[PDB]
Amino acid sequence: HTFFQKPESCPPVPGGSMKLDIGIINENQRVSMSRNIESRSTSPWNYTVTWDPNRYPSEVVQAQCRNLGCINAQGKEDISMNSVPIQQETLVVRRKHQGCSVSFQLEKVLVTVGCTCVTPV
Amino acid sequence: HTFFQKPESCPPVPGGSMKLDIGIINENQRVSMSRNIESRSTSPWNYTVTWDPNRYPSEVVQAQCRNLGCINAQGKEDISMNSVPIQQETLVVRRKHQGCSVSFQLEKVLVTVGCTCVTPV
Ligand SMILES: *[C@@H]1O[C@H](CO)[C@@H](O[C@H]2O[C@H](CO)[C@@H](O)[C@H](O)[C@H]2NC(C)=O)[C@H](O)[C@H]1NC(C)=O
Ligand SMILES: *[C@H]1O[C@H](CO)[C@@H](O)[C@H](O)[C@H]1NC(C)=O
Image (tube, rainbow over all chains, first blue to last red; front, side, top):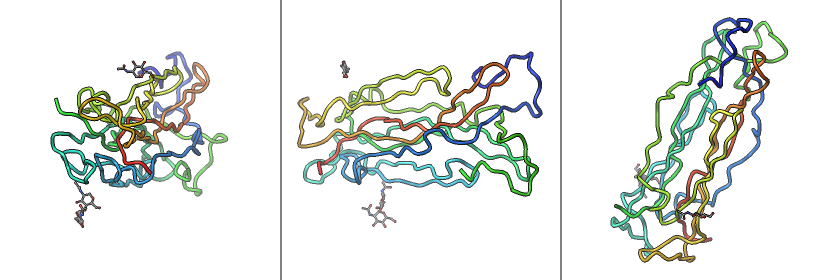
């Protein structure tokens, strides 16, 4: 909403654009999860690394649940139990235009981060 | 971060500021997961809401697995199995300065979105 604005009575800026500072705060943090988490899960998933050279991050990994149900101790799928996806709403930056008139714009993308096992209702 | 540069063959501006266009692409979307997914999951989790007025989005919801083990049909924790979190790297905007000198800078935050049930290692 009003998070990107200025008070009307402010000195104008061409294009009706805002100031985006350089540098990503915490650009260094790394995600840490169990190894092969998407295989060892009772509700395994597969990963698709979607790519876009005009988007930051360029690589956005989407997950897809491997089965309709969950896996049990034996390694068998159990359809009495459901494998459901977990969605995270995120933000990525899109790079607009060519030449020196390059600009950026926020984009909202929903990411499926993996799957969990639920009991159907 | 080479991503936010302009072609060298361009006339330099200020000291270092990019152009952020107004509007959020696809702002109209809303994550849709199973009802009470966080409770019906064999590896359930609770939600902790953090709030910061100078950040977009303001509310970043962190998740925390309720148990060490997963839960069986009966309803008891089974530590032969593990409730582990799923972490996603996201981008949030941080608001800097006040009034007309308002400026924005990207910030990366790891969000723990929910939990899945895995086999121990
Ligand atoms: C999940 O990913 C696996 C890759 O490990 C997919 O693999 C299956 O289908 C492939 C088709 O090209 C075959 O090459 C694989 O041999 C086959 N193996 C397995 C274990 O699935 C699989 O289809 C994907 N599953 C889903 C639901 O998308
Ligand atoms: C989740 O765990 C918290 C403690 O961290 C507990 O107080 C809360 O009530 C739990 N959730 C439910 C639905 O009981």
